[PDB]
Length: 300
Length: 237
Ligand SMILES: CC[C@H](N)C(=O)N(C)Cc1ccccc1F
Ligand SMILES: CC[C@H](N)C(=O)N(C)Cc1ccccc1F
Ligand SMILES: CC[C@H](N)C(=O)N(C)Cc1ccccc1F
Image 1 (cartoon, each protein chain N blue to C red):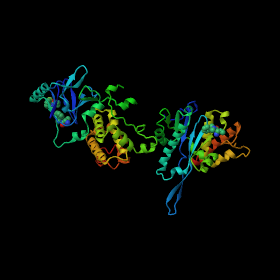
Image 2 (tube, chains in turn orange, green):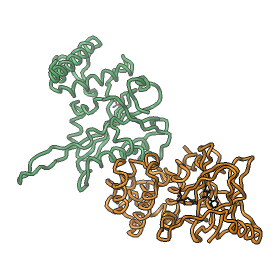
Image 3 (cartoon, chains in turn blue, green):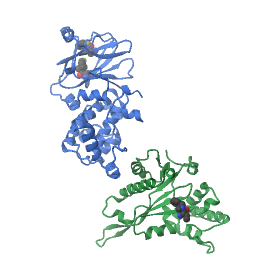
Image 4 (cartoon, helix red, strand yellow):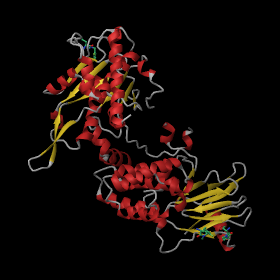
């Protein structure tokens, strides 16, 4: 079990760690979070009490380094940093723990929620979507735009999701215009899976990462990407059977975890109605259709 | 964006543009089968592709053989239309290619956009206007060449005859839309109006009669009356 320690908490802030959140008072004796499960990526995120504008956070994997948080009063945010002195870090954490200054990651033993939301998400793929190669962890916030959003303005601060565009030459084989536009299997299986992603695990990893950035930071371009990747599968008549079964599980847990009061903005009515009721895969998402109908029968 | 009453003079500027109407591409007769079920029988159709500034009409005849063994024909017809318009554009010299294509029905937007991906600078636009181009098959010479076709065929017509020697494109388009609206609302009456006077003939190379300026005013007045009459007969006013 690993630890994300904090030098202090000088400004009042709501701190999220994965799907959990807690409130820290201004100058409250707080030195971070312990008992973080090894084997998964994690996200630690922030919303200041005085400016709910800008949710921001860091994706990290404790197997890749020793990371801590320190507030910067010049840039006005909680920054993640790496401590290269392993002995120094262990000593700090041990002292923090002896003083019961670190809160406990509230993981219930029966609970597989976080695994199920991050099953295919790898830190190495995150770092190619979020480019800042001098750090082992990745910063994301509410306002960052995607490469595709920028085509339609600072590239170093962009989310380099794979561009999907149903009315593009990449999507439409010359001579198969109607075929490829009405049945996107070519684009899914040859262009994206075989060509770009290499396998369905990398595709699902990006899909899951886009959802999580949408949910935790309200990142609008990430929401667009999540829906586009769902729609590309559902609009393909020919999808490997293992992918359909896995997609149903992925979306089930995403819909299950979504805050009820955020569904209005984070769920696109057109895509979901098309995917569940009109698309080729309208009958292939039993778990997802059941939770959507019992939880959001209004949207549909 | 969409083409409507507000930006109507744009049709007659010097940027090449084409209207595309797909109404008459897929045409059927519905009938009973020996067992008492209903079936359709297709008849030849056409794409109506019109330059409103010059009157140039590229009438692509759609022969019933193009539907043989195909399913979902109303959907296929939109994609076939888009394929043929794309092929027409590619056939034209660069300086004759349109800068805009205006589709008369919004369901043509995505098919045409997808077929024209190679032409990103050609704008594909809908319209809010309710244009009467479906009545093209009430023009005798156009209906005749469509019905007689035995294979796919493109036929060229100037739909304004020689009108542009005496009137502007705006006026010609308004005359065309009036004639077609009349033919659409009451074909028999409209045609009675156009041919009542046996001394006014249709030139071999023309579509419409050789009316003098004064006779066109009379004709136009008779067509307006018809449209209002039929509007009263329909609505009881
Ligand atoms: C807002 C309730 C939150 N989801 C929760 O279940 N608890 C345990 C608060 C909490 C969470 C993490 C660390 C320390 C904490 F005190
Ligand atoms: C930080 C969330 C809450 N405001 C709080 O004060 N907790 C729950 C007490 C606490 C627990 C462990 C370590 C440090 C702590 F301050
Ligand atoms: C004898 C008049 C001749 N039919 C003519 O007007 N040409 C061919 C001009 C024209 C060119 C392209 C399409 C339609 C067109 F009408």
